[PDB]
Amino acid sequence: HMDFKNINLGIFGHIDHGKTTLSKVLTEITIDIGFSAFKLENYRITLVDAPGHADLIRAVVSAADIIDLALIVVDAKEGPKTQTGEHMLILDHFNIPIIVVITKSDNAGTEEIKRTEMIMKSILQSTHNLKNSSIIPISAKTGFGVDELKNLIITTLNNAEIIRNTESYFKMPLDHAFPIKGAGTVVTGTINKGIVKVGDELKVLPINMSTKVRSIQYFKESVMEAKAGDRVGMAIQGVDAKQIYRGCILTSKDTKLQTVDKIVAKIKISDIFKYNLTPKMKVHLNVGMLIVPAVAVPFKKVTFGKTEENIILNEVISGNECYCAFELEEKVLAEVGDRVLITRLDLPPTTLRICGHGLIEEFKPIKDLNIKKEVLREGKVKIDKGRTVIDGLAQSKVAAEKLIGEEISIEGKDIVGKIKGTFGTKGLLTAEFSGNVENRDKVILNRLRRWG
Ligand SMILES: Nc1nc2c(ncn2[C@@H]2O[C@H](COP(=O)(O)OP(=O)(O)NP(=O)(O)O)[C@@H](O)[C@H]2O)c(=O)[nH]1
Ligand SMILES: [Mg+2]
Image (cartoon, rainbow, N blue to C red; front, side, top):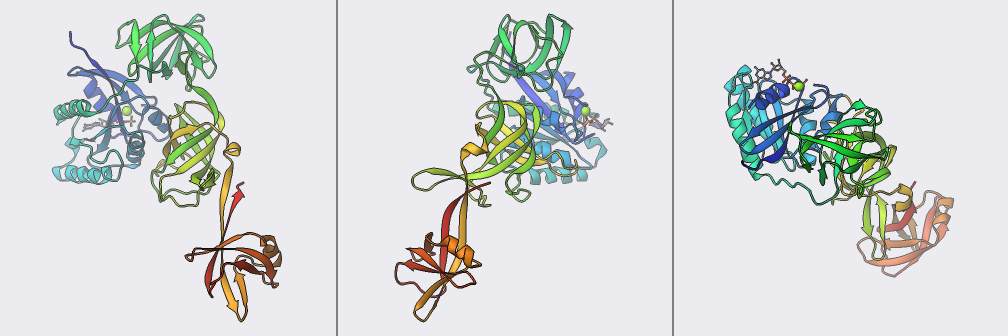
């Protein structure tokens, strides 16, 4: 017959915004994630039903790595609520195509739908990748425009660039695992990269055991081979279902995966203004399917003409370099280039909880990055009759004497000099610099410091 294409479709939104009901209406043609399937044209669509509740947002994050498309639901009448945004954020950081779906249109008037419709359009424009994503009102109960919703899901998939990675090693996470006996265990999960054929030897991590694929169940059917993008049921032998829990990852023996403690990421910030750069900060880092508490130290990479140095952020977010050395409390399974998600989940469900996202560049501890502090103190040149004295670099005599012999330039005048001695008990300074110095000139003291 015809060749089908394997598609994962997310469904996100606030609690009671009509996710599940939309799910059921699609399937026929929430603590954990829901899993279902339906066909549209030659698209085999495996539905990922995300939990609305905000204590379950761990599931929501972990529902993103799988999907190539999503539906964000929002009640017509009461419009977007708090979770609607974090789901929106999450998908936007991970560059997942969305279709905003306005549910419960039968419970609202034309006016109230148009309002909420526009409110969404306003919001979508405040997001990087989701800038303009279609919007349809539907009623799952009434069937209103459900027909269109499907025709859109088709169009969207026809446009979106879906890259199945067959080439790299087999890499697949494990959602649920349930036993049969001591010599067998069945694990489910959608395949990230690579290929598996029945009777292959793979391995569970982080526990690092070696098992063999007895069965591939895909789409309620037993097949010899599975590919990346397929959500498969998998029976393997050489492990008990007890050892395998939420964070386990099934992959081949050529894997690039590593169990990691220290992470260095290239961080982009979600909302600037909610963002703060006070280093050595306590957050909850999302890697893979886990959430590990962490400490982050933001920094930038500035070439000084010879050697590139890692400089603790000067608080300027101008230019896109907010690298972040993470140090995790627990361990985590990661690879280079894996998208990382910085969250603060300590907060109430009522406030946006995403402290940003980024690509993992290196696995490296803060200590070996050679972190350094850009150090600037600013004084003024005060000149009386026959004497030049710099003021403001030092508050007292000791502070001043410690400064003697440092580097000093004058702002805007392209001139250099050196600070020789201390003048006064109030911490003034003397210097020998190039001539043509003037009163009320600006003196910029510059040096590199050991940070923390
Ligand atoms: N009139 C109407 N009611 C709807 C529609 N979709 C959902 N509802 C109602 O909304 C309520 C919650 O629906 P549900 O799909 O379970 O929401 P959910 O997002 O799955 N809940 P959760 O976030 O807990 O998983 C139910 O009372 C359901 O009947 C719809 O299209 N029309
Ligand atoms: Mg539900």
